[PDB]
Image (cartoon, coloured by chain):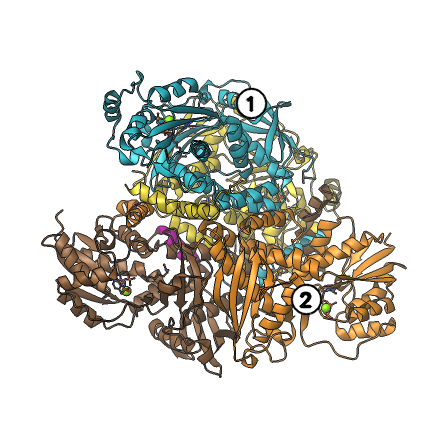
Chain colours: A yellow, B cyan, C orange, D brown
């Protein structure tokens, strides 16, 4: 008996019209909106009011920027994971959105939760794996998989029919996602990989041709694998990300133009901006090269893909992830020190690093003989053979 | 009796004095010098003549640039491997040097082979693993592990006592290696990772502040994972690497400043220049992302570290490498197409790609996939009711 | 328009009633049946006649036992793969069934292919992945996912209303699959892992208490990773498997009782009989331990899970599988020799092995190896003075 | 700087007995402290202590480490599920513990050096010395087998007699053995020919299958967080449970492995290993994991078993790499809690039921899952139209 539904509400046209749609298809159902502040830099008061004006009985706005940075982005930094060796995994936000939706749903005695992810992308998997992992008893409603709205023009017609304001502004040329960690752009003319990136895509990163002609030095202090200070100033994760995004963005750093494999089974061409992320990944990699032994570094690097795939596929809320985090946290115990980097014209240039736990500071013949003994034996057995 | 020794001879003071040293410690032994042209851009006829003036009975100069490109660098490009996710592995040349040394050693019926790799580095392992893999019967002599010479001034004293001319110009401030693929710099003041790279290190790459203010477009055509044309012009591998090294180096591309783990058990700070290698790695990665399925891409990426460690450790001549190469060659069958890149201020910027084998092209399907993909998570959370994942 | 359908036909009641059901739901479609002889040891003439009596216009019976052994089981033996470290993967037959279904469909102007795998299992994924990999243009029809028949009694009602004869003998208490490599049992009272295996499950393996009191020696010759002779007699793959299944089954060998993760999201309890497979896996493992270097063995063992998952998931017809097969075939080049084993009371006991390519054959070297192998540990403990590894 | 005191890992053999006078000879006025560990080798340790004192040791410690061997070494090993090269139960996991106790006493006694009696050709010298460097990088290590002029057992006997050490006539053991609560190892002698079956005088704790009981024996194992806590309904300490299970499973002929393994020191060795309780615990642990872990956790954990096994085999126990693996493993073991019933019979460990409070064992969706799971295969086959996967 669906009497009450919690909707992950982003403020767009689509989730706005899902409020009356949900109330139409679940008779006398009350709809509560859940709005997360992830750093998308939108007017959340206006989004809250729009949810209420659209028919929600309540509209929660939850500021999750610090929780996102400390509970999601910091473990990701520690993992060093890049999906398919290229993608900075900004959709790590989806399980956090799901977590807040489920938390509020359970305090509001709702029967079902809903989200506005489309029927063709990855985000629907991320949302629904997370919801099942957190609250297997909650019904999930995905209007894009059910309703007859097929186009933006149809959504606009429906919006006007239900008193939802639709002012004229052209269709966005690109489908975008924005949080404190990244900006993603896909769709439209981007879906043709034979074409270069158009010049109106980037939103927070300067094209290299307009970057400063003087390099900028940044000094990052890390403790146990995460950054705690910038240029000698202790900063919260959010403040450090904000400052580093501004600096590295001004210097054109961090743009990735990639073709990736979706979980749903097709390839997509995406543009990703993440200036601070690129700088943090570089500094973290340098410190690990100083502070981990060879065997630890090699084993940890061999698990980056596993971690990246888990994040990409929405499997954050799993024992598998818990076990990887426990492995990673051990490896990060001594990843503590100072990394100086020069930002300049899209480049992150090493400028020195140090750590109180730096490992940088007749035997050879015996090592060589025993290291190569199996090769010597093999070649004696296969005399005259080659390795072609 | 050791009557004949083949020496891998690079032309420095050290391998020059190894010639009388070997003749002294192996009485009446004749020494044959083997010099490889790997693209180090040195006067090899001068090096040949110095080998003979130093007491070598014969001095071979073998031009192996083409074979280095096709038999080593092209498999490396196909692998996509980077040691510790950073190093472009220019010492992939060491097994080739060992291969030419052994080939000549067997032709000349020598009793032993010798090399001048130092006793503290990786190159001695690379040479000696390769020699044992190719010719386990040959004795190996490494003078740096046997002789009493410890410093350059000690080598100079020895050279004077043994009729070896000492070059006027001193040893560079850095230990360097140079071939068509890369230039490496280590040692000296580079052994302090707390300092930035000095301004006198780079030899083939412009500093980014001194790069052109206009971008340059390059177009690379690939066939089965390797580049066959640049800007619409079919080029041999060596000509293509040469051209791309010039273009990308002019635009400041490809400098790596890293701390790596040696095989011999300690970390070293190195500077690596490899402009064309960076451009080819980028283009190859882009084309794989278009032409491989997800499962093939993910499996191949998971073997890159294995390949990189094998190359770094000198294990090129092994059945393990042969098996990896067979796997890689299958995955490269359709990595064929065109990649356009912009070179600019140290950046390699995607400018479009296409492939006749590109794999890039209902709502009811998604709900079923979601439910079964997530079923195990739903069962787990029902069993551990109320549990967190903290 | 779907005018003609090829149905993978096993001869049970369910695939029999699918023939009239397909004709009802695809207006006047012709249905041809494809029956594979995989070693299920059934009366294939009776199955062929039952397909025709049920309304099939044609019923092909294809003997695929040699193709199965040489093109599927031999690569599997070479891989050493066991799904979740326990399961011998007898459903490697499903891509072969799909391959014959498609081969015949494309000689018969067929528009759609059909199979009788249930909607809850793995086999439907295996069939339909394979069909899409081989012939993406063919439509696929799975009646269990579409029709309203939900029980055996409902199937019987439907058979009676459509002229399909109902067998006198009931449904077996277990869902079974049988080919030359294995017999699988699941469902029924087996779906309680808290209970031991009932005494009426096993079909080709003696209970251990009912095995001979004298051991039996078998001698297996291998060439390039696959068995070519048994007790000094060269035997075809099918004859060797048949003989070894009889011998090892009589000695109680090869029963696995496991809980496995399905691809479709849930765990299942299965009983698997595969006597010859257990013996061949053991002999192959022993010879690899003799003929492979350490690095090759370790790398190959690290890919067994990948291969096992690929087979289990039905991804046989993929470039990923082709690349793995290329890797594996290199590693098998020297896996050639003789393994003697004692079969006794459910045990496979090594009794000696040899190979012309066996790799089994100073104190000063050890100290240097130890010091450099341990140098990284010494540096770390000097840096972290007073620490522990708790 | 002058070596005044040496701590020696002292086993009671002839070899470490004569190392006390040898050490005192080669390090003038040095005293020798013997360190004897109780690992379950079932020897008279007070007699070994007395022999050390009689041979000239100033102090002789006997450290009972059986409980901590089980809880700090064997229990993590059981939780890992690791087998070296998929065959070896890793009984030399004891070597880092021996080194740890040696180093503790070394530091307490303010000695200048530690010594051990491992030979120059084996793995144990690496295990001891890696551990010693990881725990105490400042301590000098003395390995007399790598230094002294004693080459044979007969020479060791001559030396013992010239230095007052009792050598009564008792013939050379035909095999080199190691024994602790976890396993017994046998190698050397006629075992070094893999073409020969195991001789009938090898086994010491495991019945040959032909003399095992004719009635099966049920054991019930309760596990909590991946380790056994009770046997047949009785809570037992780890040592008591291992002792009881070794007796029961040994009586039923369980757990003998006859293998060829790759040494770290670069060559293969043929070994016989007995470990009855270990085989039973490994089987029970594997069954419980199959019930309680999700598929993705099981697959990832199984993929790290080889890493863990190699680390243990190579002596790298005292490392951050091991600590990180243990942290991963411990998370996966949090719900590996429940009851496994097994039948021991004639060398077989037969599943007889399992249950757990955390067991994970309990039409339209399947089509959508199939279509998206197989979409990349369909796209690939449309691009490579009509292609094959041979
Ligand atoms: N900050 C957020 N708070 C709550 N729900 C969110 C948030 N961001 C995304 N979602 C949910 O995730 C779904 C998918 O995100 P998204 O791709 O941004 O679509 P959209 O916001 O509906 N459309 P658009 O205007 O093009 O961005 C949304 O429909 C919401 O259900
Ligand atoms: N092109 C080459 N041809 C033949 N042998 C070579 C070549 N390059 C390197 N070697 C061998 O490898 C050894 C190690 O190389 P390297 O570190 O360059 O030492 P080096 O040339 O003797 N000294 P330096 O002058 O400081 O570069 C050399 O001594 C030679 O034995
Ligand atoms: N040897 C075979 N030849 C052709 N098709 C087969 C063969 N084995 C299995 N199949 C197909 O695979 C499907 C699933 O196999 P299976 O689980 O045995 O179902 P079934 O045979 O229809 N029912 P049952 O009588 O309980 O064995 C069958 O319905 C057929 O479509
Ligand atoms: N329980 C133990 N306590 C102390 N040291 C030990 C113990 N077991 C082994 N060691 C050390 O490990 C070394 C190698 O073990 P091992 O192979 O048993 O040689 P051994 O005891 O000297 N000779 P053997 O009588 O043939 O077993 C010994 O020489 C000791 O230094
Ligand atoms: N709803 C969105 N626009 N999401 C951005 C998707 C980014 C990227 N393709 C991913 O799947 O992680
Ligand atoms: N002799 C030399 N300078 N060799 C260059 C070594 C570069 C790098 N450290 C490597 O081991 O591959
Ligand atoms: N239709 C059948 N009876 N199939 C046998 C299934 C065996 C095993 N569970 C597997 O998926 O491989
Ligand atoms: N000293 C001994 N006898 N040790 C037994 C060695 C067992 C096995 N070969 C190993 O290296 O682990
Ligand atoms: Mg949005
Ligand atoms: Mg040189
Ligand atoms: Mg059947
Ligand atoms: Mg002993």
The chain that hosts pointer 2 is C
Residue occupying the point 63% across, 65% down: C241
**A187, B197: nearer the viewer:** B197
Q: Is residue B151 left or right of residue A25?
A: left
Q: Up-down: is C141 above or below D346?
A: above
Give the quarter of the figure containing the C terminus of chain C.
bottom left
D326 part of magenta stretch: yes
Identify the secondary structure beneath mark 2: loop
Q: Up-down: is D58 above or below A176?
A: below
Report the Cα–Cα distance between label 1 and label 2: 57 Å
Residue A235: tell me if it is visible.
Answer: no
Q: Which mark is residue C179?
A: 2
Residue occupying the point 38% across, 46% down: A371
Please provide percent x and percent y for residue D15. 23, 61
Identify the secondary structure beneath mark 1: helix
**C70, A333: nearer the viewer:** C70
**B157, D137: nearer the viewer:** B157
Give the prevailing secondary structure in the magenta stretch: helix
Discs 1 and 2 carry the same chain letter: no
Please provide percent x and percent y for residue C384. 28, 47
Q: Residue furthest left?
A: D29
Within-10-Å neighbours for mark 2: few <14, some 14–19, many 20+: some
Q: Under 8 Å from ligand 3: the CB of mark 2? A: yes
Q: Which residues are magenta?
A: D320-328
Residue under label 1: B239
């Amino acid at each position: 008996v669906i009497k009450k539904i919690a909707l992950a509400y982003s403020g767009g046209l689509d989730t706005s019209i899902m409020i009356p749609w949900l109330k139409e298809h679940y008779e006398h159902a009350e709809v509560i909106a859940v709005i997360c502040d992830l750093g998308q830099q939108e007017d959340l008061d206006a989004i809250k009011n729009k949810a209420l004006k659209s028919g929600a009985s309540k509209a929660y706005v939850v500021d999750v920027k610090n929780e996102f940075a400390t509970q999601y982005l910091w473990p990701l930094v520690k993992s060093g994971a890049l999906y398919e060796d290229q993608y900075i995994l900004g959709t790590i936000s989806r399980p956090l959105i799901a977590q807040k939706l489920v938390e509020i749903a359970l305090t509001e005695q709702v029967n079902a939760v809903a989200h506005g992810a489309t029927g063709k992308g990855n985000d629907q998997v991320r949302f629904e794996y997370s919801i099942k992992a957190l609250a297997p008893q909650l019904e999930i409603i995905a209007p894009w998989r059910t309703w007859d709205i097929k186009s933006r023009q149809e959504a606009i017609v429906y919006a006007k029919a239900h008193g939802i304001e639709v002012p004229v502004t052209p269709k966005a040329p690109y489908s975008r996602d924005h949080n404190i960690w990244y900006i993603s752009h896909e769709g439209g003319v981007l879906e043709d990989p034979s074409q270069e990136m158009p010049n109106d895509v980037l939103l927070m990163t300067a094209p290299v041709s307009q970057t400063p002609d003087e390099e900028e030095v940044v000094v990052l202090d890390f403790k146990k694998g995460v950054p705690v200070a910038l240029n000698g100033q202790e900063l919260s994760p959010v403040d450090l990300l904000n400052s580093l995004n501004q600096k590295a963005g001004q210097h054109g750093i961090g743009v990735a133009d990639i073709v990736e494999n979706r979980l749903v089974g097709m390839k997509i061409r995406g543009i990703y901006e993440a200036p601070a992320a690129a700088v943090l990944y570089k500094a973290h990699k340098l410190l690990e090269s100083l502070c981990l032994t060879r065997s630890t570094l090699h084993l940890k690097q061999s698990l980056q893909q596993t971690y990246a795939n888990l994040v990409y596929e929405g499997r954050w809320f799993s024992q598998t992830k818990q076990a990887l985090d426990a492995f990673i946290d051990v490896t990060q115990q001594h990843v503590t020190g100072c990394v100086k980097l020069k930002l300049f014209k899209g480049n992150i240039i090493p400028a020195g690093m140090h750590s109180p736990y730096s490992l940088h500071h007749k035997d050879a013949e015996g090592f060589i003989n025993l290291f190569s003994l199996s090769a010597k034996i093999y070649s004696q057995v296969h005399q005259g053979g080659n390795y072609d």
